[PDB]
Amino acid sequence: TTCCPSIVARSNFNVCRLPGTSEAICATYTGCIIIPGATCPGDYAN
Image (cartoon, rainbow, N blue to C red):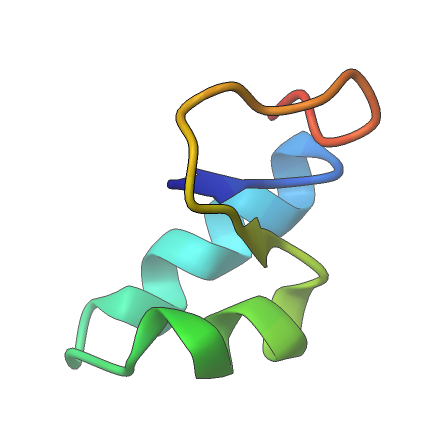
């Protein structure tokens, strides 16, 4: 599951994903994170 820190970060993440870039690279690019669970924490609410 991906969790993002802000709306901007999410929006950027989604653009990053459009060419098929792995989630992990889009994560470091944006500040979003990949977790194994499905429950994003309050500071990664977006």
